[PDB]
Image (cartoon, rainbow over all chains, first blue to last red; front, side):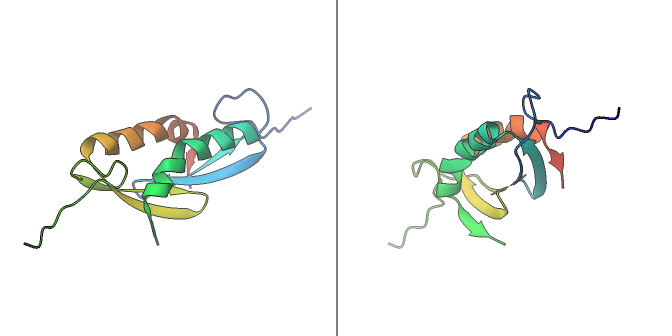
Length: 56
Length: 55
């Protein structure tokens, strides 16, 4: 059979639960992550977002 | 005197050297940072950038 899986991009340990969008230096990225890893990414960026300013 | 300073947004303590653009969950941000803190931010994102895909 042909099996198609949405795999977690960060640790590859299991399936992803969501696709998270983020950005750096004018480049936009997407990443498929478990709920746990999406939570880690959001946590890593939390204080930076709090210190930054919204722009278009 | 009117004193003007470009202040690091993250630590409020150092002089800012550059503005970094970044984004999370569909919102885009700018932040003025010392060279050291800009490197810290880019470092925090390094593992995620490497694992993710453009657009």
